[PDB]
Amino acid sequence: DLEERVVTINRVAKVVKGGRRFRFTALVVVGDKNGHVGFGTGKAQEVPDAIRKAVEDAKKNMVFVPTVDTTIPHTVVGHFGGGEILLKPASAGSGVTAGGPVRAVLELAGVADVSSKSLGSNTPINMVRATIDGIKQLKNAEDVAKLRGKTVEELL
RNA sequence: AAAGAGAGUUUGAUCCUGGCUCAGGACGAACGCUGGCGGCGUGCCUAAUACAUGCAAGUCGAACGAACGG
Ligand SMILES: [Mg+2]
Ligand SMILES: [Mg+2]
Ligand SMILES: [Mg+2]
Ligand SMILES: [Mg+2]
Ligand SMILES: [Mg+2]
Ligand SMILES: [Mg+2]
Ligand SMILES: [Mg+2]
Ligand SMILES: [Mg+2]
Ligand SMILES: [Mg+2]
Ligand SMILES: [Mg+2]
Ligand SMILES: [Mg+2]
Ligand SMILES: [Mg+2]
């Protein structure tokens, strides 16, 4: 059982001879607070039907976020097109400090204390892409030692 | 140890670039409506413009020649 959060609902149009036909596009972030999160996109003639398509789509982009002490292991920078996101660990109890669409991908992912800053564009779809582009770079300390052949206490 | 929030606006609809505007904090402040108290501070930013009237620099008879008091 996952949680839903509608980010943006936008009305788009294509021009056809007689006039204009309008459609609704919805962007939805889905995940459980344990560390899994994903996003999707839908399109329909009605707002309720656009969400349902986006929920099913979002269940195909699930990603895992590694966290230590309810905080990301280190500092990463996302990048996707014209949008980029800076994610930074923060002290316990500070809470999430994030912009509009980047809060959803962090509160749903279960991260409790993290600081961020959007250095790029403002488009909601490119902020979600640029954020997940940062979670990919995120590594745990346990796995780093495994690649480097060291042990955890030797690293730190 | 500390550690950074965005939004509106070009288009039939979109993505970028890009300016304009807004949400926060601070004044030796002024103006508008209203107005109980106590503590601690502050009060000519302009004409270094012109100034009534009072007071802000005196003291020593144990350094040297006086007036009340027989
Ligand atoms: Mg228009
Ligand atoms: Mg701008
Ligand atoms: Mg501030
Ligand atoms: Mg304000
Ligand atoms: Mg009164
Ligand atoms: Mg009054
Ligand atoms: Mg003066
Ligand atoms: Mg003069
Ligand atoms: Mg005089
Ligand atoms: Mg006097
Ligand atoms: Mg004498
Ligand atoms: Mg003497």
Image: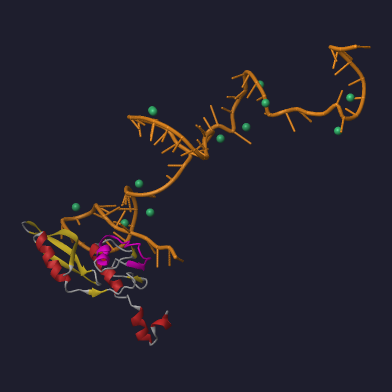
- Return the residue nearer the eye: B21 or B33: B33
Number of residue marks = 0
- Residue farthest left in this picture: A18
* Residue B63 appears left or right of B27: right
Q: Is residue A152 above or below residue A133?
A: below
Q: Residue furthest bottom?
A: A149
Q: Is residue A14 visible?
A: no
Is residue A25 at least partly visible in the picture? yes
Q: Residue at x 39, y 82 (%)?
A: A152
Q: In the rendered structure, does residue A22 fall within the stretch colored magenta? A: no
Residue A31 located left or right of residue B66 = left
Q: Quadrant of the N terminus of chain A?
A: bottom left
Residue A36: percent from left, percent from top: 23, 72
Image quadrant in which you'd find residue A77: bottom left
x, y percent for residue A32? 21, 69
**Residue A35 location, quadrant:** bottom left
x 17%, y 74%: residue: A60
Look at the image and name its color scheme: secondary structure
Going by the image, does A63 lie left or right of A97? Answer: left
Q: Residue shown at 39%/85% (left/top)?
A: A151
Magenta residues span: A85-107
Q: Position of residue B29 (x, y in %)?
A: 45, 36
